[PDB]
Image (tube, rainbow over all chains, first blue to last red; front, side):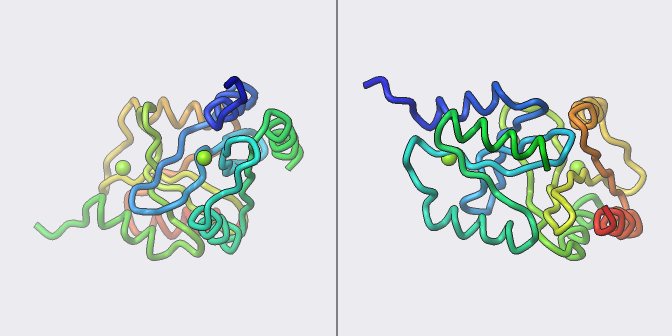
Length: 92
Length: 92
Ligand SMILES: [Mg+2]
Ligand SMILES: [Mg+2]
């Protein structure tokens, strides 16, 4: 019925980001994170999931490539987790 | 005839990046940089131009938004400028 969805979480991330929260598409590459947050401390990758939903294996594989190149990826699935992710970025 | 083009410069950037060099598209937003370089020191924006060509005003306006949010944007238009940009990122 009225449980929050992935799109709700994504809209909340956009609202709370102090900086830019740009949609990220990368033609030809599978599984890239939904958003790139641009703020004073860095540009950060964020994948948004519906409450309780894990990234698919193709998404995890892409996150691993990002981590191997040396950067982190946040996965958010609730307003609380959005708040925590943004706070961590603000303290990076 | 055989002068390097924007695509040549972009291919060279991809070849020389120590990390990921992901195509960046952001549906609904005009003028975003061509590529996001992911390496140990950060995730960085790069716009690629043909030799001697300046970013269009809509691209400059987007770069300004990125800079106001607190991050830099590199503009590369030659193999030399690619080398210099990547070296600066490796030293970030
Ligand atoms: Mg998602
Ligand atoms: Mg270009």
